[PDB]
Image (cartoon, rainbow over all chains, first blue to last red; front, side, top):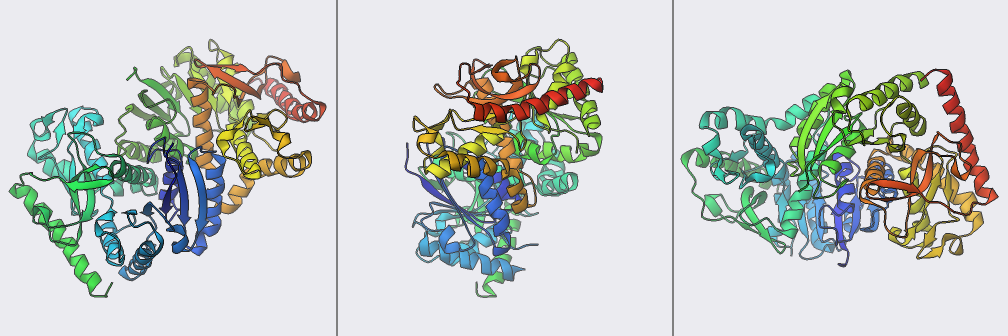
Length: 318
Length: 317
């Protein structure tokens, strides 16, 4: 019934975009009652391939796809966007990523809706989201986020498997920090069918199996498939946006990397994964948690990495 | 939260699978209240890649994915299957003969008696034929092939031309099979409750629409450097979904199903008809007036499928 919303998506002809766009047009991201207009962006070199993706989207005959355009100019892609998924990044320099997210930052602040919701997916996501909101004058910095939902989902999957519990009964999972080898999956607050996770697993498995498995999971899939985890990444992005926009379940929370306002003693400014609830299009960092020494030490090590990256970005005036 | 159903999918680590499995596991195919168990089949050389796909599905934390296994053994993949999506085919007629003879047999041996079978791998109509012929004990009526992609392509082209939403287009039909000689039918199709030819003309229908639909797959390969995996997967999902959950009232879809001899289509071949579906059963729309322009074009694929059916018999498949 609702009026259409505009969804901008970059890197739209790449593997993540190919897994992402069809499910967005199907209504899996914002609901069955919410028509979407897709505004897709690519580099000029990939525009030919992007037109092929457009033909396929058309070929699904999606009833919620209320509009569809493809461009290589950010000021057209971001034009009156309500949502902006920044999937495309440097092909793998902090130089290149810097120029992308500065350009895309100012473009968003130029032509997007004032309360546009921004999700950075391309790595390094946390620092790219930093560069982006930093160069987005007039836009609330808190509308800029980066994705740790995949680590979140990966962590949850390993816990369900270990405890013989369905994933739908795993709640209050948390991944702190950035999307990197220093990320911290937190089982001290996680619940398995209403029991504390560490009632059902002990510390040695946590430290020696669970944390390394989640942290190394991307490399394993690359090993098996000969390609990165596009589909589970895209599903993660979809859920990141969906929970942000439609709300988190009562009693639960998710991981979102957001500009730190100092909570849990995390340095201000940097984009950092927190436990969050979301309601009516707005997230709130979950307060009132107790942080022990093991958690604290690992949360600080991610923070330091992010602080290192921030001071390096500032070293280039970005 | 109904009891889970088992869904078998072959060629699971291929491009179409990679687009398929995640939407299925999410509940897009059978509904949000229907848990599924995915039983994934690949060839031995692809099992390593398939394990990667398994990891990825797990990493989505899908609440409706009640189970998940990977195997290179059809008798394992198809065990107690309620649905079977036969996506993997030859990467010729000999090779497909072996594949779909074996998979028809596996299905007979171990799948549910009322297992709904969808053949996606090309040439789908004949592969479905070989599979139902080698499936003693299963109903031939449950063996189907996909023409939903062409159907959907055709809708997309009619919508673009008339400037209306795709949701105002109903009763599209693509007769025959997934091939260049397929027949998209505008004589029965409707735009906003009006006959399509009151909104577009015969010349455009003839010289633009029909070849545009037939050449579409090639146009996508030319653009992406790869085939239509995602829209193919989407067509497969809707094929099953409409079959399972029913078609909208006043509407119908295309499905290639065993012909019983109607509409001048030789009996026994699998052939795309306009069909409705209600309660997991499909029914060919009957009593449509067919004109000679259409009949002639339908018979091209009807006769080329009949030839394939005879050619398959001569090879004892």
